[PDB]
Amino acid sequence: AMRVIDTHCDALYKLQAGKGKYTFQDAEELDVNFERLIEAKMLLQGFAIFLDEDIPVEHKWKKAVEQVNIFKQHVLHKGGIIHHVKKWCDLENLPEDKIGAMLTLEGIEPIGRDLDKLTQLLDGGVLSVGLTWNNANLAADGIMEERGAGLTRFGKDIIHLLNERKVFTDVSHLSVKAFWETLEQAEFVIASHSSAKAICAHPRNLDDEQIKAMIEHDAMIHVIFHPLFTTNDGVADIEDVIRHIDHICELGGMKNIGFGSDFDGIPDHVKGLEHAGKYQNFLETLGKHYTKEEVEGFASRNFLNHLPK
Amino acid sequence: AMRVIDTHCDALYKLQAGKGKYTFQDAEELDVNFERLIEAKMLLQGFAIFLDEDIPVEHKWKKAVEQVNIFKQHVLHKGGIIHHVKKWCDLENLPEDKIGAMLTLEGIEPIGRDLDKLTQLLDGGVLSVGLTWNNANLAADGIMEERGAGLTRFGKDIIHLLNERKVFTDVSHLSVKAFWETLEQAEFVIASHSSAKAICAHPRNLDDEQIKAMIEHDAMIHVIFHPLFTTNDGVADIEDVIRHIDHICELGGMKNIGFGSDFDGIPDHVKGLEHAGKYQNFLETLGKHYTKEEVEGFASRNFLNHLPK
Ligand SMILES: [Zn+2]
Ligand SMILES: [Zn+2]
Ligand SMILES: [Zn+2]
Ligand SMILES: [Zn+2]
């Protein structure tokens, strides 16, 4: 039984937007639903808290908390199997029949200038935080901001707290400058859903020096199943995804690769990776390029070897 | 009788903080109150919209609308004499017995990332906009942010809107980088309350190169009545303020100088200038140093030669 850790899906965002017309148990419009987790044989799934950039700055904090309660009410205890991983020890002591679920924060927009709002979310079980989504915010510039500046003092204050609380600092949407400053400050670095710039040149992807630095830093790179970041022409199959894994391995990152699908946040899908239920198929295909020992590394063992401590 | 244009006071912030306790007509706590505007022979006073940095992000818009309402309800029409300058033509056509009052925005924090909220403020009469106060925000870094970055996409979009609406872009608290990028983007530039760094080396002040650039751009520099920005030692009298005026004149900016007191935002005052009712005393001292025609330039004519058109 090849169990799977996936670091990033947008199920919370989709449920929230759905206004009840979607049930987490079996909605077919959700790449990540309860049935599809079982079928994926998930060990752990990360659920991102993420608000539309058009949610007014003064409603952000309320809508975030709402997504959290959607998690607590809809996702948790589903079928008596979904278990809340609120701390890394909850993960290391999870049963074989239970599936772990954790919360992650995709941009700090919901917290304004307030570190107590962040502390609240951390007390709620948030185990990974990305300072930015695509845009400039109070902590740093995201990757689509042309200015591409690094961290503010507020940003550094945030990371200092993440370090203190054994929470991942997620660089996936971070500007190039922010990424580098973050590596300097953060103790536990992850890229929750990124691929390799050398294979697909989207600004969102990691260049070779950044990948080497991640490896050197002992950080995790979780490759994304989004075709816009997989191939330059934006149309991709499973083999295309594998070419990104190949690239990171050739840079020496065999032990630093995991999966970060970005399921439910995908406008278009990779052929054969249409939803979390297609996971074991993906692993079988992967298994023609990598030993089972290596695939298990990508699937869960690398991540489990990199828990904040 | 020489009339006075002053581009910047914090009466709205004080009024709001006073929680109804301060009457605009004559409160001693208000550096700019009605009786003192009369004594000053004010022609036009700028009223800044400014929130404590500690106001949570989700309440900023509300607190700002509060200040606009304070302006409309406590300031306008007082004595049948205070007249709303909502557009520049209201200023050039002010009836003889009237005193003009205009709104300005001291940092774009209250609008979140919503350009429409800015459009509302502009429609309500904001005629000058500083992108930042001291801190990083969604538009640019302020002068006290270590990162010291320039304009974001949002900041550039704001300036385009200000250009189109014939509104001043105010660089008084902008980071050095943001200052230079703003001179590039903004059609109508002002420093609503800033002095000369060569005289007083505070980081908020303008160095000779910046001043020469302001003059070249045909921008207005309004000298401040804050001791902290007036003398290196923080203790100042009227003659100390005049040194800044002299300095700018020497750089060739006699026609680009006006006044920006920052009254009501000053913990300790320039001796002799403790409130707006001392303004004529100020002009009397200027008159030792400059012809009457030159003093009228600083007091109002210069600003009146620089209205956005
Ligand atoms: Zn997302
Ligand atoms: Zn995303
Ligand atoms: Zn102010
Ligand atoms: Zn100020």
Image (cartoon, coloured by chain):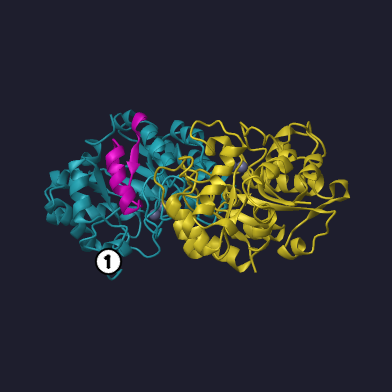
Chain colours: A yellow, B cyan
Determine if residue A219 is in view: yes
| Number of marks | 1
In the visual, does B188 lie left or right of A168?
A: left
The chain to which mark 1 is attached is B
Q: Which quarter of the picture shows residue B285?
A: bottom left
Residue type, mark 1 in image: Ala
- Residue B269 picture quarter: bottom left
Outermost residue toward the bottom in this view: B233
Is residue A268 or residue B190 the one in the foreground? A268
- Whole-percent x and y of residue B124? 46, 33
Farthest residue to the right: give it.
A80
Does residue A208 sit above or below A243 in this rendering? below
Residue range in magenta is: B163-192
- Asked whether residue A169 appears in the rendered view, the answer is no
Query: Which residue is labeled 1 in the image?
Result: B236
Q: Quadrant of residue A122?
A: bottom right
Q: Is residue A198 left or right of residue B181?
A: right
The spot of residue B84 in percent (x, y) is 41, 34
Q: Is residue A92 left or right of residue B258?
A: right
